[PDB]
Image 1 (tube, each protein chain N blue to C red):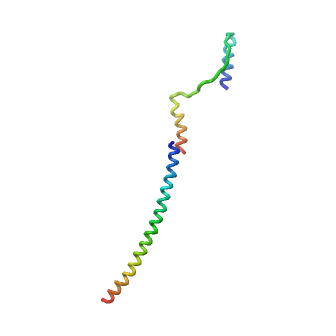
Image 2: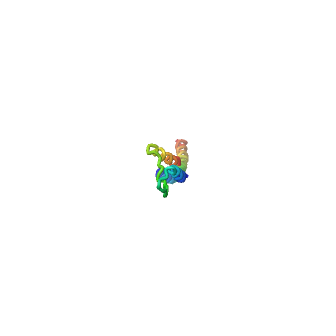
Length: 56
Length: 52
């Protein structure tokens, strides 16, 4: 029983590990897109700051 | 080979006696190891399962 029970657990651990891999991959790309959008806003914002400072 | 030897040897043992007893069958019943060492005998098998 300890042999068959342990073997079944191996499959279960493999399945749970596989799911986490996909989950991490999806989260990874999401963070990249979020960072890209935030970076774009900062670039556009910097343009406005330069104009105001130059005008003043 | 034992049930053959012990049966043959037992017959030779009673040949000089000349008694009228006749041997019909010699059927071995059990050869279990001592109960004190039985514990280890089963553990050796469990170790193979534990190895797997």
